[PDB]
Amino acid sequence: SFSGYLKLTDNVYIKNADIVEEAKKVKPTVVVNAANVYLKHGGGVAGALNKATNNAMQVESDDYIATNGPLKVGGSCVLSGHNLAKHCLHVVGPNVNKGEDIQLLKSAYENFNQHEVLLAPLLSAGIFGADPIHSLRVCVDTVRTNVYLAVFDKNLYDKLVSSFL
């Protein structure tokens, strides 16, 4: 199971880790992807998860978009986890660098409540432009299921833990 996590609340845990490496080690039931509405996994967490699947995540995602159209900001879809997990929950957090409504971050985290346990990144953090401290607060105040957060950046992980109210 998950090892080396710091417990923040009854249901939220955090670790300084690369989520791709964490997924390959744990092979959790659900890994969360920091997706965009088009499921174009170019950079950040999505690019790293897709590259780990040898682009199979992108091929599956393009077929999903061709059939269903784009996701909504704040929405999600469940696809295969390929070699990383049983399932990948592609969740679209608001991209602040695209002027998307930061209020949609709570709706994005609500998707996690449909899964008993998840390995996830902080939504809208990184290249999505939101404040990761704010993302962690929305996470602990919205998610009720067991969420294991993987924060790639050590300096950000330390800042998140030391500032956690």
Image: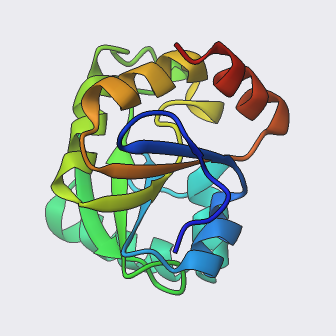
Residue 37 visible from this viewpoint = no
Looking at the image, is 122 positioned above or below residue 85?
A: above
Image check: 92 left or right of 82?
Answer: left
Image check: 119 left or right of 126?
Answer: left
Along the line of sight, which residue is nearer the eye, 109 or 51?
109
Looking at the image, is 161 positioned above or below residue 47?
A: above
Query: Residue 112: image x %, image y %?
Result: 27, 48
| Count of marks overlaid on the render | 0
Along the line of sight, which residue is nearer the eye, 59 or 26?
26
Query: Residue 80: image x %, image y %?
Result: 35, 79
Q: How is the image coloured?
A: rainbow
Image check: 128 left or right of 28?
Answer: right
Looking at the image, is 120 positioned above or below residue 84?
A: above
Residue 31 location, quadrant: bottom left
The residue positioned 38% from the left and 59% from the top of the image is 118
The residue positioned 53% from the left and 86% from the top of the image is 83
Query: Residue 58: image x %, image y %?
Result: 48, 72
Looking at the image, is 125 positioned above or below residue 31?
A: above
Residue 108 visible from this viewpoint = yes
The residue positioned 63% from the left and 79% from the top of the image is 24
Along the line of sight, which residue is nearer the eye, 145 or 151?
145
The residue positioned 68% from the left and 58% from the top of the image is 4
Residue 12 location, quadrant: top left
Along the line of sight, which residue is nearer the eye, 99 or 33?
33
Image check: 3 left or right of 71?
Answer: right
